[PDB]
Each structure stands twice: as C-alpha cells, then as structure tokens.
Image (spheres, coloured by chain):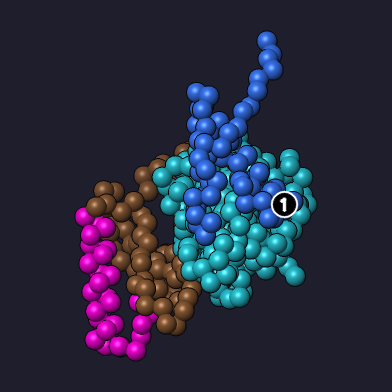
Amino acid sequence: GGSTLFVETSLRRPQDKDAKGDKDGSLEVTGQLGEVMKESARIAYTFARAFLMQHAPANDYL
Amino acid sequence: GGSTLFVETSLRRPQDKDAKGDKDGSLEVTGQLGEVMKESARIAYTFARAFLMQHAPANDYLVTSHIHLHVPEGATPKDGPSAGCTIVTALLSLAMGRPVRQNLAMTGEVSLTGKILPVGGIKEKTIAAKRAGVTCIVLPAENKKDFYDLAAFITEGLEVHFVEHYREIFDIAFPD
Amino acid sequence: LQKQVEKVLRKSAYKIVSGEAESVEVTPENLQDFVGKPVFTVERMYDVTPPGVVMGLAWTAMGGSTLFVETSLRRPQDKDAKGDKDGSLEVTGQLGEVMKESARIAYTFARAFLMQHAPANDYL
C-alpha cells in the first residue's frame, strides 16, 4: 500500500566554522538509499541551493 | 529504442565567493556516470571553457563557478559519449543565460578540440526526435549517409544540420 | 572485407536466381546498391592538425592505429601577471600509472625545452 513518510533534516555541524570560510555545505543522507536515490537527493540539494540563491541571495545557510 | 534525454545544468554554489578568487570552477556530474562518460564530460567541460575564452573572454562564469550537470541515464555505455556535444552547449547556455533554440536536438562526440565524431543509433535517435516533435536536428557529417539511408517519410520537417566542428553548432543553437 | 565481399556476392546471387540479370559485372557505380553508401569517408580525423594536437601511432591489440594526442588550455593563461603559480596539468584517456609518470616526465621535459629555446614563453 501507501504510507505517509516524514523527510527529516538537521544541521549536524555548527554553521560558522570560519566566517571567511568559503567551504562546501556537505550533505549526509540515510534511509538505506540506493545509487539512483543518492543521485536524486544530490539533484534536489543542488536545486534547493540554486532556488535559495535566486529567492534569498543573502541566505548562505544551505 | 531511442529517447530524447534533457541534459541539464545548474549553479550549485554561488558564482562570486571572492571577486579576487582564483579558485577553479569545479564541475559535478550525475546520471550513473561511467568512467568513459566521466572522461568525456571532463573533455566537454574543458572544451567549453576554452571556447568561452576564445569567444567571450570576459565571461568567467564557466572558469570560476561550481556547477552540477545531469545527463539522464538509459543510453548504452558505448553511446554515452554521444551526449558530449549536448553537454557543451548546455554549459555554454548557462554561461550566457541564452536558452538554446526551441525544438532543437543534437548528438555528437567532442574530442577536446571541438571536432565532432560519428555516433551510432542514428535511425533510432531520429525516430525519437520525430516522435518528440523536434524539427531541427544536429548530427556529425560522418553519420550523414546513415541519415540519408533512411526513408523520406521519416525525415519530414527535420531541418537537418550536419557539422564536423562544434563552432557551427554555436552558430545554430545560438543564432543571435 | 570478407563480410563485405560475401554481402555483395549474396546480393549478386539473389539478382541472378530471381533477378533479371543472368550475370553480374560489379563496378563502383553499381557498388552503391550492392553494399550501400561508403562508411569511412575520411582517411583520418582531419588533415590540418591545429595547434596543440599532434598525430601519433599506437600498437593496440587489434593491430595498429593513428591516435591524435590533443591539448587544450582549460583555464585562462593570466589569472594575475604577478601570479607565480605553476601550470598544473590534467590528463585523460584511461591513463595508467606508468603512463601517468611518463606524461609527467614529458611535461617537465617540454617545460625545460621551452626554457632553453624560448625563455620569454612562460605559457607552459
């Protein structure tokens, strides 16, 4: 059948290691994910980053 | 059979981390990439970079920007490199923001200098193009006979565009 | 070549048994219908060899071949005229470890050769 799952997200490391730091916001994913699911999650992550840079350019959270 | 896969690109990290910044514009590729496909994507990326310097030197978008490109999977590995040409224009569009001309399809293999090599499955790809509504298609000149060995009733409305070097395609997809 | 000759002979046999022609005199003019349009229209990838690309010979498993070693500038030459950073090299082609070392050796030798023959050329 179907189900109502919950996709959860959390910040597993402090936001500001170095205010000057220009490092990547690496993403860790679980859920016994397959390769195609990992690629889909990566695509969604990149799209979210682009959407934020379009809508909230000052929000460097993601 | 054949298919019409949309190679996509996006800027997964802000362009100007540092206006002075001299860091490299990394590229990340998805689509169940194989090793040969990884190398072909790198070749296409380098050719697009060099083409941008030659044509639009002031455009540092491709040199300094971290990009993610997705090539949809499904193509047999031997035909994977045939997406190379596509990749190039994709990136170039993202660099200049100019959308590629509508109802235009293309398949080709780049060789780090822009020259386009023959490919396989021309008939199936043409069938997919016709079924997808595209009216302008791009193929390497070396495949031209394979496109001319087809029936007439399968090539109506296909304003074919044969090429041997990528420059021509930039004059087709980006007319103005 | 055996496959192609067998194909033309098979089509000649068809043209003989049921076809009007009792005998066949194959010529290039007729050849287009016996086997189709030519495949290998070019003797090579090209005949100009633009800058940064050179032809070479390879002893592959399926005999010999002519492979074009290509080069491109994958990053602008002058990030900063003062900039003293070295010209890192990227390489592809399923390069092996020993081939990676050989490519590095060739890169350094080319750099030294330019040093000797054209010191003003800091390109490489």
> Does the image show residue A56?
yes
In-image side of B46 versus B167 (left or right): left
Between B16 and B134, the one nearer to me in the picture: B16
Quadrant of the rendered image containing residue B13: bottom right
- Rendered-image quadrant of the N terminus of chain B: top right
Looking at the picture, tell me which residue is in the foreground, A9 or B142: A9
What residue sits right under mark 1 in the picture?
A: A56
Q: Quadrant of residue B168?
A: bottom right
Q: Amino acid at mark 1?
A: Ala
Chain corresponding to cyan in the figure: B
**Quadrant of the image for the C terminus of chain B?**
bottom right
Q: Secondary structure at mark 1?
A: loop
In this picture, which residue range is highlighted in magenta?
C98-124
Task: Tell me, by letter, which chain the rendering colours blue.
Answer: A
Q: Position of residue B47 (x, y in %)?
A: 51, 64
Q: Is residue C75 above or below residue C120?
A: above
Tell me residue A12's x, y (percent): 52, 36
Name the residue at 48% across, 63% down.
B24
Q: Residue at x 50, y 40 (%)?
A: A13
